[PDB]
Length: 175
Length: 172
Image (tube, rainbow over all chains, first blue to last red; front, side, top):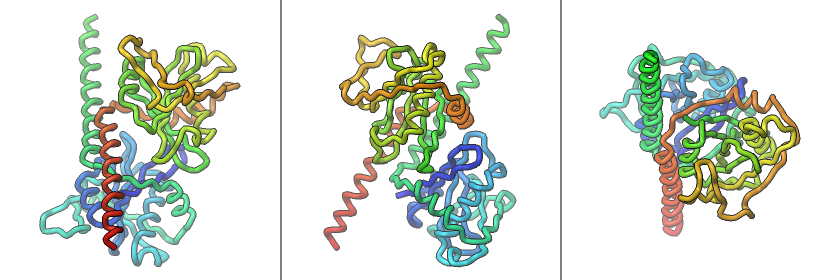
Protein backbone atom coordinates (compact mmCIF):
# COMPACT_ATOMS: atom_id res chain seq x y z
CA UNK A 1 0.00 0.00 0.00
CA UNK A 2 1.25 3.44 -1.04
CA UNK A 3 -0.04 6.80 0.21
CA UNK A 4 -0.67 9.66 -2.21
CA UNK A 5 -1.06 13.32 -1.19
CA UNK A 6 -1.72 16.44 -3.27
CA UNK A 7 0.45 19.56 -2.90
CA UNK A 8 -1.10 22.66 -4.51
CA UNK A 9 1.28 25.42 -5.63
CA UNK A 10 0.82 29.11 -6.49
CA UNK A 11 0.09 28.44 -10.18
CA UNK A 12 -2.91 26.19 -9.38
CA UNK A 13 -1.14 23.01 -10.53
CA UNK A 14 -1.37 19.93 -8.32
CA UNK A 15 1.80 18.02 -7.51
CA UNK A 16 1.58 14.34 -6.60
CA UNK A 17 3.44 13.11 -3.51
CA UNK A 18 3.64 9.45 -2.55
CA UNK A 19 5.06 7.58 0.42
CA UNK A 20 5.41 3.88 1.13
CA UNK A 21 3.93 2.19 4.17
CA UNK A 22 7.15 0.51 5.32
CA UNK A 23 10.55 -0.59 4.05
CA UNK A 24 9.37 -3.32 1.65
CA UNK A 25 6.85 -1.19 -0.25
CA UNK A 26 9.66 1.38 -0.51
CA UNK A 27 12.05 -1.22 -1.94
CA UNK A 28 9.74 -1.33 -4.96
CA UNK A 29 9.20 2.44 -4.89
CA UNK A 30 12.99 2.65 -5.30
CA UNK A 31 13.06 -0.02 -7.99
CA UNK A 32 10.19 1.43 -10.06
CA UNK A 33 10.40 5.19 -9.52
CA UNK A 34 10.04 7.51 -12.48
CA UNK A 35 12.65 9.97 -13.79
CA UNK A 36 10.15 12.71 -12.88
CA UNK A 37 10.38 11.67 -9.21
CA UNK A 38 12.29 13.55 -6.51
CA UNK A 39 13.34 11.57 -3.43
CA UNK A 40 13.17 13.28 -0.03
CA UNK A 41 14.62 12.02 3.25
CA UNK A 42 15.53 13.52 6.61
CA UNK A 43 19.29 14.07 6.65
CA UNK A 44 21.38 12.10 9.16
CA UNK A 45 18.25 10.60 10.78
CA UNK A 46 15.85 7.71 10.30
CA UNK A 47 12.70 8.62 8.38
CA UNK A 48 10.36 7.54 5.61
CA UNK A 49 11.25 8.22 1.98
CA UNK A 50 8.90 10.79 0.46
CA UNK A 51 8.57 11.09 -3.31
CA UNK A 52 7.38 14.05 -5.38
CA UNK A 53 6.48 13.48 -9.03
CA UNK A 54 6.92 16.48 -11.31
CA UNK A 55 5.17 17.36 -14.55
CA UNK A 56 6.55 16.70 -18.02
CA UNK A 57 9.51 19.01 -18.60
CA UNK A 58 9.93 20.10 -14.97
CA UNK A 59 13.30 20.10 -13.21
CA UNK A 60 14.32 19.66 -9.58
CA UNK A 61 15.63 23.22 -9.27
CA UNK A 62 12.25 24.55 -10.50
CA UNK A 63 10.13 23.05 -7.71
CA UNK A 64 7.85 25.68 -6.10
CA UNK A 65 8.91 26.51 -2.56
CA UNK A 66 5.49 25.66 -1.12
CA UNK A 67 5.66 22.17 -2.63
CA UNK A 68 9.27 21.70 -1.49
CA UNK A 69 8.25 22.59 2.07
CA UNK A 70 5.25 20.28 1.80
CA UNK A 71 7.56 17.38 0.97
CA UNK A 72 10.08 18.46 3.62
CA UNK A 73 7.51 18.80 6.41
CA UNK A 74 5.82 15.57 5.32
CA UNK A 75 9.08 13.61 5.42
CA UNK A 76 9.98 15.24 8.75
CA UNK A 77 6.67 14.37 10.42
CA UNK A 78 7.21 10.73 9.42
CA UNK A 79 10.61 10.64 11.14
CA UNK A 80 10.86 8.99 14.56
CA UNK A 81 13.18 11.68 15.95
CA UNK A 82 12.88 14.36 13.27
CA UNK A 83 9.23 15.03 14.03
CA UNK A 84 9.91 16.00 17.65
CA UNK A 85 12.83 18.29 16.70
CA UNK A 86 12.41 21.91 15.67
CA UNK A 87 15.20 22.24 13.08
CA UNK A 88 15.94 19.41 10.65
CA UNK A 89 17.65 19.07 7.29
CA UNK A 90 16.14 17.15 4.38
CA UNK A 91 18.19 15.86 1.46
CA UNK A 92 16.38 15.44 -1.84
CA UNK A 93 17.75 14.13 -5.13
CA UNK A 94 16.27 13.00 -8.46
CA UNK A 95 15.17 9.37 -8.45
CA UNK A 96 17.64 8.69 -11.27
CA UNK A 97 20.44 9.57 -8.81
CA UNK A 98 19.49 6.78 -6.38
CA UNK A 99 21.85 3.79 -6.37
CA UNK A 100 20.89 0.39 -4.93
CA UNK A 101 23.52 -2.35 -4.61
CA UNK A 102 23.35 -5.96 -3.47
CA UNK A 103 25.50 -5.19 -0.41
CA UNK A 104 22.79 -2.78 0.80
CA UNK A 105 20.04 -3.31 3.36
CA UNK A 106 16.30 -2.76 3.01
CA UNK A 107 15.60 0.97 3.31
CA UNK A 108 19.27 1.90 2.90
CA UNK A 109 19.96 3.73 -0.36
CA UNK A 110 23.00 5.22 -2.07
CA UNK A 111 23.67 8.01 -4.54
CA UNK A 112 25.22 8.02 -7.99
CA UNK A 113 26.47 11.59 -7.45
CA UNK A 114 26.36 13.76 -4.34
CA UNK A 115 26.46 16.74 -6.73
CA UNK A 116 22.74 16.44 -7.55
CA UNK A 117 21.76 15.79 -3.92
CA UNK A 118 20.24 18.99 -2.53
CA UNK A 119 19.65 20.20 1.01
CA UNK A 120 16.87 22.20 2.65
CA UNK A 121 16.33 23.02 6.32
CA UNK A 122 12.80 22.87 7.69
CA UNK A 123 13.07 25.18 10.68
CA UNK A 124 9.89 24.47 12.66
CA UNK A 125 6.76 22.30 12.84
CA UNK A 126 3.69 23.66 11.05
CA UNK A 127 0.48 21.66 11.38
CA UNK A 128 -1.53 23.17 8.51
CA UNK A 129 0.84 21.63 5.95
CA UNK A 130 0.28 18.14 7.35
CA UNK A 131 -3.47 18.60 7.91
CA UNK A 132 -3.98 19.96 4.39
CA UNK A 133 -1.72 17.23 2.99
CA UNK A 134 -3.57 14.39 4.73
CA UNK A 135 -7.02 15.70 3.82
CA UNK A 136 -5.88 14.74 0.30
CA UNK A 137 -4.57 11.31 1.37
CA UNK A 138 -5.54 8.50 -1.02
CA UNK A 139 -4.37 4.93 -0.42
CA UNK A 140 -3.59 2.73 -3.42
CA UNK A 141 -2.12 -0.71 -4.10
CA UNK A 142 -0.46 0.01 -7.45
CA UNK A 143 1.52 -2.25 -9.76
CA UNK A 144 4.44 0.13 -10.21
CA UNK A 145 6.21 -1.84 -12.96
CA UNK A 146 3.15 -1.56 -15.21
CA UNK A 147 2.60 2.11 -14.34
CA UNK A 148 6.23 3.00 -15.00
CA UNK A 149 6.08 1.29 -18.38
CA UNK A 150 2.90 3.25 -19.09
CA UNK A 151 5.08 6.30 -18.50
CA UNK A 152 7.76 4.84 -20.77
CA UNK A 153 5.16 3.96 -23.41
CA UNK A 154 3.78 7.50 -23.20
CA UNK A 155 7.27 8.93 -23.72
CA UNK A 156 7.91 6.62 -26.68
CA UNK A 157 4.60 7.68 -28.23
CA UNK A 158 5.54 11.35 -27.87
CA UNK A 159 8.96 10.77 -29.44
CA UNK A 160 7.49 8.79 -32.34
CA UNK A 161 4.85 11.53 -32.62
CA UNK A 162 7.53 14.21 -33.03
CA UNK A 163 9.40 11.93 -35.44
CA UNK A 164 6.26 11.49 -37.54
CA UNK A 165 5.42 15.21 -37.65
CA UNK A 166 9.06 16.09 -38.42
CA UNK A 167 8.92 13.63 -41.32
CA UNK A 168 5.62 15.30 -42.20
CA UNK A 169 7.37 18.68 -42.21
CA UNK A 170 10.52 17.55 -44.00
CA UNK A 171 8.39 15.82 -46.64
CA UNK A 172 5.83 18.63 -47.01
CA UNK A 173 8.75 21.09 -47.22
CA UNK A 174 9.06 19.80 -50.79
CA UNK A 175 5.36 20.70 -51.25
CA UNK B 1 -2.64 13.31 -28.03
CA UNK B 2 -4.96 13.84 -25.05
CA UNK B 3 -5.43 17.03 -23.04
CA UNK B 4 -5.52 16.93 -19.23
CA UNK B 5 -6.65 19.80 -17.01
CA UNK B 6 -6.70 20.07 -13.22
CA UNK B 7 -9.81 21.31 -11.43
CA UNK B 8 -9.08 21.96 -7.75
CA UNK B 9 -12.13 22.21 -5.52
CA UNK B 10 -12.62 23.64 -2.03
CA UNK B 11 -11.72 20.26 -0.49
CA UNK B 12 -8.17 21.01 -1.67
CA UNK B 13 -8.16 17.81 -3.79
CA UNK B 14 -7.37 17.98 -7.50
CA UNK B 15 -9.77 16.43 -10.00
CA UNK B 16 -8.37 15.24 -13.33
CA UNK B 17 -10.18 16.22 -16.53
CA UNK B 18 -9.19 14.90 -19.94
CA UNK B 19 -10.35 15.65 -23.47
CA UNK B 20 -9.37 14.13 -26.79
CA UNK B 21 -7.88 16.06 -29.67
CA UNK B 22 -10.52 14.95 -32.18
CA UNK B 23 -13.28 12.38 -32.67
CA UNK B 24 -11.10 9.35 -33.45
CA UNK B 25 -8.82 9.79 -30.45
CA UNK B 26 -12.03 10.06 -28.44
CA UNK B 27 -13.12 6.71 -29.89
CA UNK B 28 -10.26 5.23 -27.87
CA UNK B 29 -11.13 7.42 -24.90
CA UNK B 30 -14.61 5.86 -25.14
CA UNK B 31 -13.29 2.30 -25.41
CA UNK B 32 -10.79 2.58 -22.53
CA UNK B 33 -12.44 4.93 -20.04
CA UNK B 34 -12.40 4.02 -16.37
CA UNK B 35 -15.44 3.34 -14.15
CA UNK B 36 -14.35 6.43 -12.18
CA UNK B 37 -14.91 8.57 -15.29
CA UNK B 38 -17.85 10.93 -15.82
CA UNK B 39 -18.65 11.80 -19.43
CA UNK B 40 -19.69 15.38 -20.27
CA UNK B 41 -21.12 16.59 -23.58
CA UNK B 42 -23.16 19.55 -24.79
CA UNK B 43 -26.78 18.42 -25.00
CA UNK B 44 -28.48 18.57 -28.43
CA UNK B 45 -25.37 20.09 -30.08
CA UNK B 46 -22.08 18.82 -31.48
CA UNK B 47 -19.16 19.23 -29.09
CA UNK B 48 -16.08 17.50 -27.74
CA UNK B 49 -16.37 14.74 -25.15
CA UNK B 50 -15.02 15.89 -21.78
CA UNK B 51 -14.11 13.36 -19.09
CA UNK B 52 -13.75 13.81 -15.33
CA UNK B 53 -12.00 11.05 -13.40
CA UNK B 54 -13.22 10.64 -9.83
CA UNK B 55 -11.34 9.42 -6.79
CA UNK B 56 -11.65 5.97 -5.24
CA UNK B 57 -15.07 5.79 -3.64
CA UNK B 58 -16.52 8.84 -5.38
CA UNK B 59 -19.94 8.84 -7.04
CA UNK B 60 -21.41 11.03 -9.76
CA UNK B 61 -23.90 12.66 -7.39
CA UNK B 62 -21.06 13.68 -5.03
CA UNK B 63 -19.14 15.85 -7.51
CA UNK B 64 -18.39 19.32 -6.08
CA UNK B 65 -20.26 22.07 -7.89
CA UNK B 66 -17.07 23.95 -8.83
CA UNK B 67 -15.68 20.84 -10.54
CA UNK B 68 -19.00 20.08 -12.26
CA UNK B 69 -19.10 23.64 -13.62
CA UNK B 70 -15.45 23.39 -14.67
CA UNK B 71 -16.28 20.33 -16.77
CA UNK B 72 -19.49 21.92 -18.07
CA UNK B 73 -17.87 25.23 -19.02
CA UNK B 74 -14.92 23.37 -20.55
CA UNK B 75 -17.21 21.22 -22.71
CA UNK B 76 -19.21 24.28 -23.79
CA UNK B 77 -16.10 26.25 -24.75
CA UNK B 78 -15.08 23.31 -26.97
CA UNK B 79 -18.47 23.30 -28.70
CA UNK B 80 -18.68 24.87 -32.15
CA UNK B 81 -22.07 26.46 -31.42
CA UNK B 82 -22.28 26.04 -27.64
CA UNK B 83 -19.49 28.55 -27.02
CA UNK B 84 -21.31 31.38 -28.82
CA UNK B 85 -24.52 30.78 -26.84
CA UNK B 86 -25.30 32.18 -23.39
CA UNK B 87 -27.48 29.30 -22.13
CA UNK B 88 -26.54 25.69 -22.91
CA UNK B 89 -27.31 22.26 -21.46
CA UNK B 90 -24.62 19.71 -20.62
CA UNK B 91 -25.42 16.03 -20.15
CA UNK B 92 -23.03 13.91 -18.09
CA UNK B 93 -23.22 10.19 -17.28
CA UNK B 94 -20.87 7.58 -15.83
CA UNK B 95 -18.54 6.07 -18.42
CA UNK B 96 -20.01 2.64 -17.63
CA UNK B 97 -23.32 3.95 -19.02
CA UNK B 98 -21.84 4.70 -22.46
CA UNK B 99 -22.96 2.30 -25.20
CA UNK B 100 -21.11 1.97 -28.51
CA UNK B 101 -22.40 -0.28 -31.30
CA UNK B 102 -20.98 -1.13 -34.71
CA UNK B 103 -23.76 0.74 -36.54
CA UNK B 104 -22.83 3.90 -34.61
CA UNK B 105 -20.87 6.81 -36.07
CA UNK B 106 -17.55 8.23 -34.90
CA UNK B 107 -18.30 10.56 -32.00
CA UNK B 108 -21.91 9.36 -31.85
CA UNK B 109 -22.36 7.59 -28.51
CA UNK B 110 -25.34 5.85 -26.94
CA UNK B 111 -26.53 5.17 -23.41
CA UNK B 112 -27.36 2.01 -21.52
CA UNK B 113 -29.97 3.90 -19.48
CA UNK B 114 -31.20 7.48 -19.79
CA UNK B 115 -31.86 7.41 -16.01
CA UNK B 116 -28.16 7.56 -15.06
CA UNK B 117 -27.65 10.46 -17.50
CA UNK B 118 -27.76 13.77 -15.64
CA UNK B 119 -28.24 17.29 -16.97
CA UNK B 120 -26.98 20.71 -15.91
CA UNK B 121 -27.56 24.07 -17.57
CA UNK B 122 -24.74 26.59 -17.77
CA UNK B 123 -26.39 30.02 -17.76
CA UNK B 124 -23.37 32.23 -18.47
CA UNK B 125 -19.91 32.43 -20.03
CA UNK B 126 -16.99 32.54 -17.59
CA UNK B 127 -13.46 33.15 -18.88
CA UNK B 128 -11.70 32.69 -15.53
CA UNK B 129 -12.76 29.03 -15.41
CA UNK B 130 -11.25 28.38 -18.84
CA UNK B 131 -8.14 30.48 -18.19
CA UNK B 132 -7.45 28.77 -14.86
CA UNK B 133 -8.14 25.37 -16.45
CA UNK B 134 -5.84 26.21 -19.38
CA UNK B 135 -2.95 27.22 -17.10
CA UNK B 136 -2.94 23.61 -15.87
CA UNK B 137 -3.03 22.01 -19.33
CA UNK B 138 -0.89 18.89 -19.70
CA UNK B 139 -0.82 17.00 -22.99
CA UNK B 140 0.06 13.31 -23.00
CA UNK B 141 0.19 10.47 -25.54
CA UNK B 142 -1.01 7.68 -23.25
CA UNK B 143 -1.55 3.99 -23.90
CA UNK B 144 -5.03 3.86 -22.41
CA UNK B 145 -5.35 0.07 -22.50
CA UNK B 146 -2.23 -0.29 -20.36
CA UNK B 147 -3.27 2.48 -17.96
CA UNK B 148 -6.76 1.01 -17.53
CA UNK B 149 -5.06 -2.35 -16.90
CA UNK B 150 -2.98 -0.66 -14.22
CA UNK B 151 -6.24 0.51 -12.67
CA UNK B 152 -7.75 -2.99 -12.82
CA UNK B 153 -4.53 -4.52 -11.48
CA UNK B 154 -4.57 -1.94 -8.67
CA UNK B 155 -8.13 -2.86 -7.69
CA UNK B 156 -7.25 -6.57 -7.81
CA UNK B 157 -4.30 -5.90 -5.48
CA UNK B 158 -6.51 -4.04 -3.01
CA UNK B 159 -8.87 -7.01 -3.09
CA UNK B 160 -5.99 -9.37 -2.28
CA UNK B 161 -4.88 -6.99 0.48
CA UNK B 162 -8.22 -6.99 2.28
CA UNK B 163 -8.78 -10.71 1.61
CA UNK B 164 -5.55 -11.76 3.29
CA UNK B 165 -5.94 -9.09 5.98
CA UNK B 166 -9.18 -10.67 7.13
CA UNK B 167 -7.56 -14.07 6.62
CA UNK B 168 -5.00 -13.01 9.22
CA UNK B 169 -7.73 -11.24 11.22
CA UNK B 170 -9.39 -14.61 11.80
CA UNK B 171 -5.94 -15.95 12.78
CA UNK B 172 -5.63 -13.32 15.56
